[PDB]
Amino acid sequence: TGGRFDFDDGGTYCGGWEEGKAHGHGICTGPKGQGEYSGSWSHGFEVVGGYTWPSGNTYQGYWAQGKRHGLGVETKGKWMYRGEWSHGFKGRYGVRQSLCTPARYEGTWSNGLQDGYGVETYGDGGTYQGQWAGGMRHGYGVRQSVPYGMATVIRSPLRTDFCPVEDHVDATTTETYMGEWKNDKRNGFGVSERSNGMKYEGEWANNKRHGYGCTVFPDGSKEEGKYKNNILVRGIRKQLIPHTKTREKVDRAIEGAQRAAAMARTKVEIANSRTAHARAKADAADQAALAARQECDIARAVARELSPDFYQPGPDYVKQR
């Protein structure tokens, strides 16, 4: 059977029911009539259907225990996510993609944040591949710039593709960083190398050379010792009449950076695997979203027949967006 029920909070359920619970197809609006689910129900819970927020953003896919769960597609402003959901949040595997450019992330997620392994393609076409935690590049991974003249101009200290931006560059130069990241920044041991032959091997903090390391310039000359915020503050040479161990500390930092770069390459391989599984789950989510739109159409017709004057707000939400 079917019916219309009002909740104390101002929302409504209109649709099929059995044993005092939503069952079959039906529409349910949120408190004060804001937000709308339209789709199938089993024993009080959504199963396959669409949610529309007042902004016009939508989720179309599967549900469990009252939440987005399993495969589904979310459209939120200029970003769409296709893939798996768990207890209302993105994950484990899926793809978030821009509606108008190739910028995207493919890989794993935790609680709606990029987390585990994956690859982000930035607006300029450059990438990060490797480990993520809590939405941030964190662990080991590789940053690949595009040519400098094409790369997005971002202020220091947030910029991560060319670090630092200084005069050993031309419009064609690219930069790669392979090594450790902390909290979205180059931090710890790592190697940066440019296509003009410049290279730094050593320690980083806050996207800057910081600690011991060696820079080789395109002409083959070197600057090495202890860096503070990208500035060399102690060189290798001892004073005329001196104990210090700068030479040894630089050599140990170079070794640490080369090991971290190798580890980052290992993490890239895992991240590439995760992106292939994420793309497969995104394609599966496209099918889940189609099923949800079909169930939504049935639910709209059921509620229109039961309660012709009940306002289903979802279509107008999308129209006004």
Image (cartoon, helix red, strand yellow):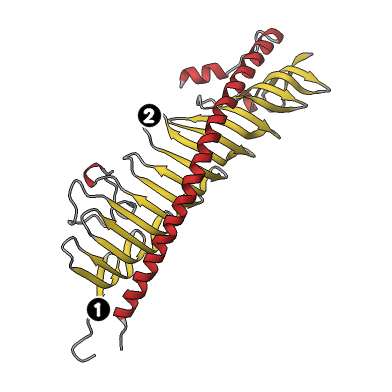
Q: Residue furthest bottom?
A: 241
Task: Residue at 36%, 60% (x, y): give it.
Answer: 206
Q: Are marks 2 and 1 in contact (CB under 8 Å)?
A: no
**Which three-letter amino acid code belongs to the residue tagged 1?**
Ile
Task: Residue at 46%, 22% (x, y): give it.
Answer: 321
| Along the viewing direction, whichever of 221 and 245 lies nearer the viewer | 221
- Which residue, given by chain and number where applicable, does mark 2 sit on? 100
Where residue 119 appears, x then y in whole percent? 44, 45
Count of number-bearing discs = 2
Residue 44 falls left or right of residue 253 = right
Residue 135 in view here: no
Residue 138 falls left or right of residue 224 = right
Quarter where residue 307 is shown: top right
Q: Residue furthest right?
A: 19
Where residue 154 appears, x then y in whole percent? 29, 47
Cα–Cα span, label 2 and label 1: 51 Å
- 10 Å crowding of disc 1: few (<14), some (14-19), many (20+): some
Where residue 272 appears, x then y in whole percent? 46, 46
Q: Secondary structure at mark 1?
A: loop
| Numbered circle sitting on residue 182 | none
Quarter where residue 16 is shown: top right
Residue 291 falls left or right of residue 176 = right
Decide which of tag 2 and tag 1 comes sooner along the chain.
2
Q: Secondary structure at mark 2?
A: loop
Task: Residue at 50%, 34% (x, y): give it.
Answer: 81
Where residue 233 appears, x then y in whole percent? 25, 73
- Which residue, given by chain and number where applicable, does mark 1 sit on? 236
| Along the viewing direction, whichever of 48 and 218 lies nearer the viewer | 218
Q: Is residue 82 above or below residue 155?
A: above
**Which three-letter amino acid code belongs to the residue tagged 2?**
Cys
* Eye-nearest disc, 2 or 1: 1
